[PDB]
Length: 326
Image 1 (tube, one colour):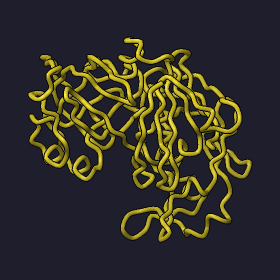
Image 2: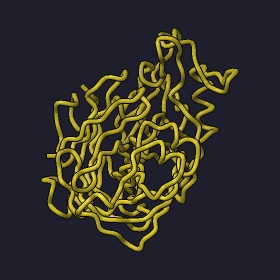
Image 3: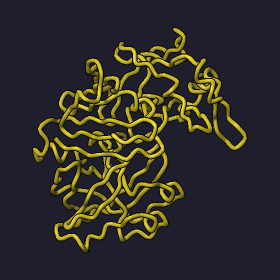
């Protein structure tokens, strides 16, 4: 039973620490269920984003070992380029021996420069892994370093502490009620089927169904740009002066509940949740992002939805289990 604490960053970015090499070099990474690769900046990276963050120096790890393999990854926000190498990764109190991870050479762009995080640790299916690189949780399960072939995650609300990723375990301490399990549509992302999206007893969206991934590496609740128009129009969101869609922070009171039906089970989203706010100003947690796929336009269930529902990712039976947090 591994335990990896996470830092809640402005209810927008949840990262955690890891160590790579011997002695171990520390790095803060994002635990991304929307990605499957693990990469940290390296000392052979001259990009403004690596100078800005910690750089893994293989020359100082006695258990490091190289490859000829190049790796490349595209994110809806960042881009990356590097080489693959093996070393021992320390996660949630578990020594992940012979883990293949990438070492950056380029981290192009503006966005990876302003980030409080150094790298990314994907928790999705090896199906979408760049360079067919073995994900961490797969390497843990394979080396029998975890008792169960599942992991669970708890995300903190209002900047509080308490955010955690439980490797090979489930803790009833985090949810109320019973664990509802939903089968996985398509193995790649943490892909689930949504049946509908309601408000006021009205199906404001996702009629006849839609696809959604459960991504802890996305901050807002995401969907096709036309579809969300309907939602923002409904909660009274406004694309303001500076380029944002805020809302009268007091208009939370009137506002009904947006409800998501998954596998026929109702999963409500209270306005205290779908509306982000600083005691100065209120935004919408809904974001339009057209994400085409063979399956269709993806809806992403990000931190707004995950903060309210304790999620279990079961690789054994390929299902996602949900339950309201405590």
